[PDB]
Image 1 (cartoon, rainbow, N blue to C red):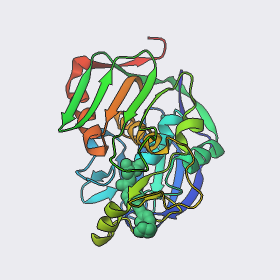
Image 2: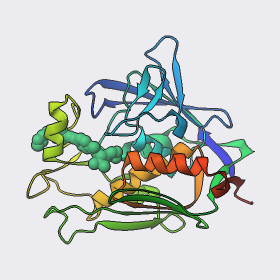
Image 3: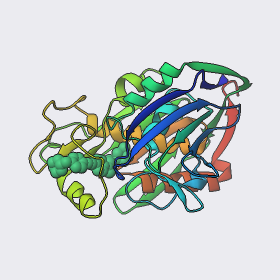
Image 4: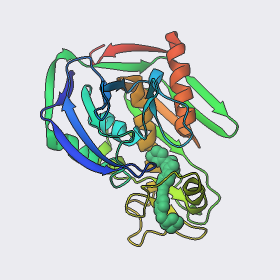
Length: 287
Ligand SMILES: C[C@@H](O)[C@H](NC(=O)c1ccc(C#Cc2ccc(CN3CCOCC3)cc2)cc1)C(=O)NO
Ligand SMILES: [Zn+2]
């Protein structure tokens, strides 16, 4: 009902998944109507980039926010955690151009946010409510918003790989009955060994390891300790979608369905929705 921020400042450290750079992350409370703002504190002047669809850059690997010649790479997992915990306002300070990958999931971030504490603010919380279907497609990929009285995220993947043979590749999460933390937050990012070796040849995925990603070779999951969920891969796609959806700037009242979608198509959906003014409205929980 009311806007939420952090109660205290909290710090964490990690490595950027693509850049491999050590990064210091500081989450800070922020005033009412700030939204989630990334701050590049290594730069003078400090560059603030609100986590909004208009600040997304063209990047095929992850969601990247850009302002001038400055970027903040790989924001989706931390944004998913902000969205999952209903954090309206926060500054996310970074000492480098990439959010740390942590364990590849939103687990460390949801724990970090809860550890900082939650602070109720003196302003009504606003939600973006989907009023009509908005859909984007490209080839076999689709991402759609549908009106829904609540918040629901559906995803389907379809990989031609034996690890995916008979494995859950579709999942739907209705957040009125399911906990973001319990069933989505711990889902780790994943990569196919071929895709990974190719990113490595482009000097990308430098901070990647079996400690922060599920690595799938031609036969099996390489990670010795296995999966956190039988449907971990599709649950991570849901985690990614929730982070991308949070670039709308407010919690969503609606349903998202993704069909082999990724950050590029998710962002195209956000832009089409915003441009389609009659397809959405910004409302309070009471309204
Ligand atoms: C939708 C998601 O697929 C998407 N994830 C990514 O695109 C993504 C994930 C992980 C990585 C990585 C990595 C990495 C892991 C291990 C090794 C070491 N070895 C290399 C050879 O095999 C044995 C191990 C090197 C690098 C790269 C990219 C996402 O979550 N977007 O949000
Ligand atoms: Zn991801």
